[PDB]
Structure formats: structure tokens, C-alpha cells
Amino acid sequence: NATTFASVYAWNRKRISNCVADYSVLYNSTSFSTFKCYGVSPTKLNDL
Amino acid sequence: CFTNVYADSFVITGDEVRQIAPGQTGKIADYNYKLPDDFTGCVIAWNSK
Ligand SMILES: *[C@@H]1O[C@H](CO)[C@@H](O)[C@H](O)[C@H]1NC(C)=O
Ligand SMILES: *[C@@H]1O[C@H](CO)[C@@H](O)[C@H](O)[C@H]1NC(C)=O
């Protein structure tokens, strides 16, 4: 939830250090049209 | 030919229809519907605006 995102050609990688990854907070905040995980299952993201 | 059939009809938004697959997570797949792992069925969806 930011004012501006990067352009696709200047795509601005950033890292996420010590914090708890709880995707539950975005349930009424945003609606995701695509959510595809590779090498991991979406139902195991809470146990990892 | 099938020996038993069920329906399970409801209404969600268009962005959440992807969450009605077996191994999905999200607001609907976590707190609302939650299909099982060995489903053996078909999932039908269509816009109804
Ligand atoms: C969540 O979304 C609903 C629907 O727009 C809104 O009424 C509510 O204020 C939002 N926040 C919370 C904490 O429910
Ligand atoms: C997202 O950005 C909006 C800016 O309009 C802000 O009002 C809101 O508090 C931010 N956070 C959430 C969870 O919506």
C-alpha cells in the first residue's frame, strides 16, 4: 500500500528482514487476483 | 453414473473464485468454504452482475 510503485524496467528489489509474515491483515485491505507459489504450498506459509 | 451428488451454491466476488480450489488460502478458503484435499468433483462459476 504505497503511493507509487516502480516501473517494470526499474523494478526496485527490497528485502524483508526480522518480522512475522501474516498475510491475514490484507484480507479486507486488498483483493489479490493472482497468488501463485513455487516450491512451496500456500497452506504451508504459516508453518515456515 | 454417480451414486451421490451435492450442490454447494454461494456467491463471492470475481477475484475470489480462484480460492475455490482444493489447496488454496485466503479470506474465503480460510474462514468461509475450504474445499477438501481429495475433492472428486467439478467447480462451476459464472459472472452474475
Ligand atoms: C474492512 O472492510 C469493510 C468493508 O469495506 C469495512 O467496513 C471495514 O471498516 C474494514 N475494516 C475492518 C477492521 O473491518
Ligand atoms: C492504505 O493506504 C490508504 C491511503 O488512501 C490509507 O488510508 C490506509 O490507512 C492504508 N492502509 C490500509 C490497511 O488500507
Image (cartoon, rainbow, N blue to C red):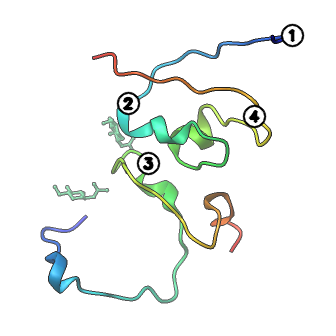
Q: Position of residue A27 (x, y in %)?
A: 44, 48
Give yes or no for contact between labels 1 and 4 (Cβ–Cβ under 8 Å). Answer: no
Q: CA distance from mark 3 to mark 1?
A: 38 Å
* Residue at x-position 13% and y-position 76%: A7
Given the image, what chain letter belongs to the residue carrying mark 1? B
Q: Position of residue A10 (x, y in %)?
A: 16, 85
Given the image, what chain letter belongs to the residue carrying mark 3? A
Label 1: which residue? B3
Q: Secondary structure at mark 3?
A: loop
Q: Position of residue A34 (x, y in %)?
A: 40, 54
* Residue at x-position 48% and y-position 89%: A17
Given the image, what chain letter belongs to the residue carrying mark 2? B
Q: CA distance from mark 3 to mark 4?
A: 25 Å
Q: Residue B39's mark?
A: 4
Q: Amino acid at mark 3?
A: Tyr
Position of the C terminus of chain A, as image quadrant, is bottom right
Q: Secondary structure at mark 2?
A: loop
Q: Amino acid at mark 4?
A: Phe
Nearer-N-terminus badge (1/4)? 1
Nearer-N-terminus badge (2/4)? 2
Q: Secondary structure at mark 4?
A: loop
Q: Position of residue A25 (x, y in %)?
A: 45, 56
Same chain, marks 1 and 4?
yes
**Within 10 angstroms of label 3, few (less than 14), some, or many (20 or more) residues?**
few
Same chain, marks 3 and 4?
no
Q: Is residue A5 above or below residue A36?
A: below
In front: mark 2 or mark 4?
Answer: 4
* Residue at x-position 38% and y-position 44%: A28
Label 2: which residue? B13
Q: Is residue B15 left or right of residue A48?
A: left
Label 3: which residue? A27
Q: Is residue A8 left or right of residue A24?
A: left
